[PDB]
Image (cartoon, each protein chain N blue to C red):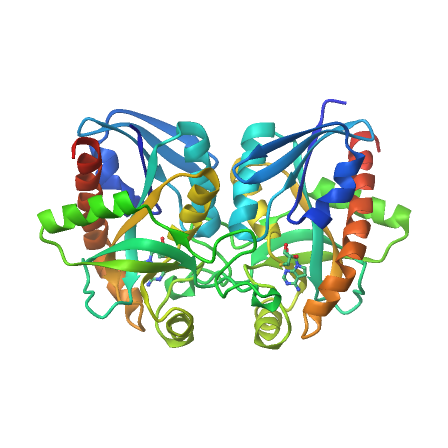
Length: 232
Length: 234
Ligand SMILES: CSC[C@H]1O[C@@H](n2ccc3c(N)ncnc32)[C@H](O)[C@@H]1O
Ligand SMILES: CSC[C@H]1O[C@@H](n2ccc3c(N)ncnc32)[C@H](O)[C@@H]1O
């Protein structure tokens, strides 16, 4: 099997990239795809860049080109659920755009025409992720992750997300775009990210200071997840 | 005679007229998108129906570029008019595209800019000139300028006000142009947006859209046909 992995920033893909053996690099459409094996498992790691379009472009390339069996979106996120603290894990059971609005025509807030109002992550991928979380003794929350093309740091931006998606556990900028692409190609996906901040008026400083920590936690989780999917 | 022109429209109504005119037409269904190949007035074209929104347009544009390698991309369809002299049916030609809903300002990026990208994506000068030549020849009313995109249908109120305040110079607003420009930019492919006005993005936009979408589609499609011809023969 081939496992696809997508991270947005250098920090979020560098540790995994350093571990890929029989590594080959593909530079294309402004993205980088690293192919090879992670602890014996065939993977394809994509550094997509930040934002929905960058992520959609990279996911599309990855699916069309390398044709992985499942997609795992790694990286950092702004924590919204009460029990989350920096470094904690968020596992998507679903992804929705918090900034899409075509309600003028009767679509659900966050829903784009031609798409489900939310994209569901794969149950097996979620089960495997949670088994790893238990085995590594990590604090994690499973639930709705919302994406938009904006960095959230309190004020109006956070307020609007709370209103439309009070049950969202985390917010970031690529997951739902990746889920949307996977949905169109019928590819299972799961988002496994780590908290770099709590999306408030202090998230800039928190993100700056804890991104490396969040990237590491999510990377270790992905490493464990890949191994679990490949060997049980 | 060796040029392949890529054309991207989001909705059925926006691509149907051009599609019916493609000779030796074939249909490719990939990634939830539909691409029609063949010739338009003898010029090789690849017409994609992308679906609505930034991600749907990005996915489609990426497929079209990777799969059909067109030499240039023309984004067709409707838009909400923002510049004063625009009436329903008029043409808007992009000289630039920017996301009106992207905000990473907390980190010092320009409003609308995503990290790793230029704050705005510039349309091709030759494609712009050709489109304007077509405009002068069809004797249509048009405006050239900044087109801004977002994943929201602008219906007046705060959505509209925020846009006018952040991009006072924007001539129109829609939902796919900048995502297509972004993908084209990353692939180094020349692009131009030539859309037509279906509404003025105000509280009436919902009704105006339902009523004049066909008119915008007709006017934009005429422009695209003329542009394809212009680009291949002069
Ligand atoms: C530098 S923009 C923030 C990047 O980290 C993720 N991230 C982390 C925290 C966070 C937040 N509070 N709001 C939005 N995106 C966030 C996003 O997916 C994007 O790739
Ligand atoms: C049914 S969503 C609107 C569709 O038509 C375009 N459009 C036209 C007018 C308009 C507006 N006022 N606001 C946003 N998108 C608009 C968009 O790019 C999208 O494909």
